[PDB]
Amino acid sequence: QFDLIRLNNGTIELNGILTPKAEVLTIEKTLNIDELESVHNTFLTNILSHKLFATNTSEISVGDYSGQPYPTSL
Amino acid sequence: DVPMSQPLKEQEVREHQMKKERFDRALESKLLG
Amino acid sequence: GEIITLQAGQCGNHVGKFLWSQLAKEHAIGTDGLSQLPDSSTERDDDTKPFFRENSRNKFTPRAIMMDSEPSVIADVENTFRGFFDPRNTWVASDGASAGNSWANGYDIGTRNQDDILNKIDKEIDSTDNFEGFQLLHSVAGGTGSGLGSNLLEALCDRYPKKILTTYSVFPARSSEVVVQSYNTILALRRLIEDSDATVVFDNASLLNISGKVFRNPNIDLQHTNQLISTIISSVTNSIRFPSYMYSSMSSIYSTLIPSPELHFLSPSFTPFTSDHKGHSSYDVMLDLLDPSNSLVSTAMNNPTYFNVYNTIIGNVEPRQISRAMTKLQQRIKFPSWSSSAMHVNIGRRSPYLPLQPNENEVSGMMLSNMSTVVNVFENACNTFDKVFAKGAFLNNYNVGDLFQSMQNVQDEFAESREVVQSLMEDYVAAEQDSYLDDVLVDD
Amino acid sequence: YDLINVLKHLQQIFLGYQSGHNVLKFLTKNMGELTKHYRNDNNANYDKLLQNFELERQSENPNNLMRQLLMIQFDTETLPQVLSHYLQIYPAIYHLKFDINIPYPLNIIISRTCMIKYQIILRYQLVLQYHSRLLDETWMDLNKTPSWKYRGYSHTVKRRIVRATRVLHAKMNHFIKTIMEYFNQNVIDKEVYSLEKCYRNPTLAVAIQNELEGGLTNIMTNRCLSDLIPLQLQIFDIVYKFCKFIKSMRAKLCQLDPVLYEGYQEDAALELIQKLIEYISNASSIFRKCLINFTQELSTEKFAAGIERVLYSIVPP
Ligand SMILES: Nc1nc2c(ncn2[C@@H]2O[C@H](COP(=O)(O)OP(=O)(O)O)[C@@H](O)[C@H]2O)c(=O)[nH]1
């Protein structure tokens, strides 16, 4: 039941306020349309966020000794 | 009429409590207050 | 650390019946192997796993191998524990009854069945991931009992060289049967001295000295007093079953109990208790425990040397009481000049399901110690042995299997077994002397 | 929120209250994994232990949020460096620590102050458990591996090396556990009862917050964290060293005794005996110096039940 966010620093964050139990003093985590699209975009982005595919940016380390983006060599 | 000292337990308690306080104050500072 | 109980001979199986009964009470599990608890509360605040193969089902299977030559003792237990025990872990020496009360007979049947016995042991080890060890329940002078224990021990000490196999040795009061029973004791004891892990001594004489006061007399019977044996066993594992945060392992337990590679036979004591417990203070329980009147071994010494003293108090213990008791105990224990006296005191827990728990504002507990006089439990057997197996019928006509390949393997096995026992006694005595380490630690 | 359940979970995690069971299973699995990062190692490859942790965490009942949120992280200062700073202890092993992202609203009571104190307590206890566990393994080797079987080395080895090793070891086992029993019984358990009895049927949120931090401070202020750490550290170095000496040197000694070595007939084994004797004599001396210094420090509090029990286990007959 716990909605937990894993962070890269090891933190597991509860996603929001911890709610009380059903016993109180006095539902489903479904996705909406944008959320579904977002998940999909996130996914494709993640594939292409892998370092080896970053051929459109100066941020890709261009190999090391070859001096080229990994896909050039591949 | 005489140069009498303060209470012994009270001083012991204060030494204990002051130690506790110094420590907690140091921790509060690291947490930036 | 998973533990497998080995129930050998009728004594071992009768003792197990009491042990498992107490465990079923401690962990509210029925005789059918089911939790007695509602499942409305899924957290039990205990761990039955080391003793039971809790199933995916509401089933707790005792981690035990039931072994005998006489299937009726096992059946008496299985027929009580109607679903609790797994019958596939039951072995009976069906290929001939033991030829009388000789460890050799028990040994010979175990030897022939050694592979089958081990297969059952491994079927249960296969149900344990973190297997740590075994608990062997047996009489010391029974044919099937000590013989099976001798076979089990030889098979297991080599097959599982890194696992812990402890022994729960039940000693008959010495009587005329000793002309056979002392060699069963002595030769099976040789095997224990050489191969067994820490062993605890239960002297039937003391079970009776005590049961004559605490059991419903006339039934103060040794198979009835298995509750006293069970009380000690369950007390020892209480730190495992309802673990606290200090001692959670057998290896941790023995780290302060075993001073050398020598097998030590330890002497338990216990007071007060409830079974089918209102002590006043832990102060008093600890002090009361350092008294032979609460002992299950009739060492009867006024000034024995103690080594490795440990006790566990379970209940609402006040640390001030504990400290005061240690203060005085520290001043009145005999121990060698070469070792500071360190008493180890552990605090345990009452089962959350113990029916007594809601009204327990009282404490009780157990003491275990390494006594230079623990060996007194073997004295009458030894003196008998020296006079009887030097040359009597008792030496050769009770031997079967390898023990009687020739008389030579009798004459020397018996003499050597006596010597192994003599050495055990000599070392308990050597440890009483300052010279034990004065000829060690300043030898440079 | 069942705050009490949350709290027992927290206690089980950082005090290890009633959880020696879980301390041991994790500690044992990773016992040898606590040997390298502090030896000046810029260890960025302990991900395997991190993963072992996560895998173990995954086995826990999901209802226990406090376990579900637990994380392993590393520091730059080891426990005694941290303590010397905070307790103004007249001034190097283990950078590991755990935390929990305590969610709102419960984090209003379980403050960061509480959590940092919890890390300190836990690290302290884990260190003691580490050394205890090393000693537990050590007697298992000494009294089980057939080095105990050596005879063919004479009494000139049996006494001054074998009995000497085993007794020094036992003294150490008794010392470490005595201290641990003290800490857990005279420090941790009483604070836990305080928390439960201060609770019972509480009237003030503040009182709860107060006792929680209060007890944790009382622990932080324990003489064992304040005054005695420098010697505990000497003992810890001693335990580690003797435990690593054992098994390795145990095996080496087999070359002298034909019961295992049988080939051998070398002065090298005789050199081994002399090395073992000198090592052991020094081993005894440094252990005793620590015990002496320890005893002496305890004796100067200018006056203790939890101290007297410790001294009892130390002071020679
Ligand atoms: N305390 C105790 N003693 C027992 C029990 N059962 C039998 N004895 C003792 O066991 C000794 C011999 O071993 P036993 O297992 O009974 O016989 P075996 O099956 O033929 O080996 C006898 O001297 C009895 O006094 C028991 O359950 N508890």
Image: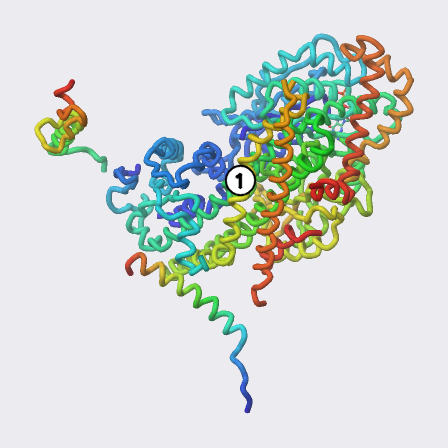
Residue at the image position 91 percent from the left and 18 percent from the top: C391
Q: C22 or A71: which is nearer to us?
A: A71
Residue D158 percent location from the top left of the image: 70, 33
Q: Residue at x 63, y 50 (%)?
A: C363
**Residue drawn 50% across the image and 52% down it:** D188
- Its colouring scheme is rainbow
In the rendered view, would you say C13 is above or below D278? above
In the drawing, does residue B17 fall left or right of residue C114?
left
Residue C312 in the image, given as x and y percentages of width and height: 63, 45
Question: Which chain does tag 1 point to?
Answer: D
For the image shown, how many numbered marks are present on the structure?
Answer: 1
Tell me where residue D236 appears, x and y as whole percent: 52, 45
- Mark 1 sits near ligand 1, with its Cβ under 8 Å away: no
* Observer able to see residue D121: yes
Specify the quarter for ligand 1. Answer: top right
Q: Which residue is mark 1?
A: D241
- Residue D160 versus residue D184 in the image, above or below: above
**Most foreground residue, C107 or C33:** C107
In the foreground, D278 or C373 = D278
x then y, percent, for residue D306: 58, 56
Residue C370 located left or right of residue C115: right
D23 lies left or right of C358: left
For residue C140, side relative to residue D101 (left or right): right
Q: Is residue D193 visible?
A: no
As drawn, C322 above or below C419: below
**Circle 1 crowding by C-alpha within 10 Å: few under 14, some 14–19, many from 20:** few
Q: Is residue D278 above or below residue C404?
A: below
